[PDB]
Image (tube, rainbow, N blue to C red; front, side):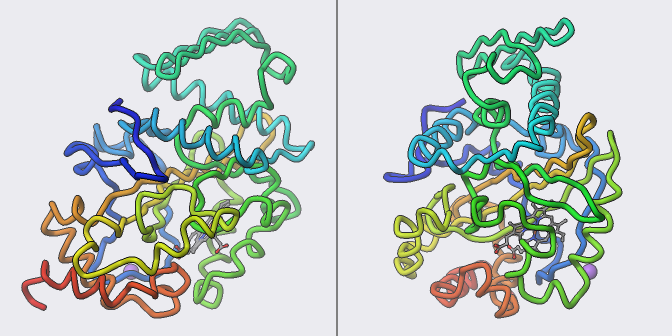
Length: 334
Ligand code: HEM
Ligand code: NA
């Protein structure tokens, strides 16, 4: 854990060379198109973000401080409908188990029956509590555990052949809101997305997710861009960030424009049968990213050729020409 970084104000967030090397670059081809890009979420590539189900990295402490700040200002970024309380406990169990198993230097879990002992040495938390008893924790169980894991989480109720967004912790969204989407179904919350409905992508994706079973979780990557390493790109806070999209110039692309990648986990929760959706969000500046000449060239092509409805949906319009011009310098064939 490096010294405390900000994702707001002075934006002191930066990647080490190791964090650059393991950034989940999300483009398998020189152009991007939506698809059902799901795979089994099996451990692979030691040191990579695909090694564990829940990835904890050098920015862990920084990110939990940012989450704490978002929540100080807006506690309503976390919602658990009453029927999702058991799902919220399942979530806490799954996170604590995996974290204590995968990062034993930082986390520990000892249990006897519902008497649990959790230590988070990274954040200096030493908690004896009762599993299932919300009065034994200093807050609601989803909020308790997600204040201690990177990325966002939605918790979906599976009923009536559909998935409903009935709980979550959403403090670093790519321009959407859990309070808006609360209680929506899978096609409904995806209603703003261009093209993918007509292509069948959301039909097929629902069908795959509905069949996810215990111990066979699934993953995919999503991506966008963000000006500055701003994690809280929410509607709630638009006045704080939306105007930065007007500040990009040919001289500052490399410092301002960041590639934002979500490593998404879909895992069946065993007591409730709810589906956990982990949104693990990574940020990299274009200066950092162009370290890697292959990534630079490929990003140039992707951004040059991206369908305009996708570009526009992703919020990249206002600065896209400046960006493409900048990136062209890293593409010899162009
Ligand atoms: C329970 C699982 C999921 C949740 C909670 C979720 C949630 C969301 C949300 C809230 C958005 C933003 C919509 C907006 O603009 O307001 C979104 C966008 C999107 N989702 Fe999902 N989603 C899930 C699973 C899937 C899967 C499996 C796919 C498979 C292809 C997918 C594809 C997309 C696409 C293509 C976009 C637009 C993203 C972009 O262009 O950057 N989602 N999702
Ligand atoms: Na393809």
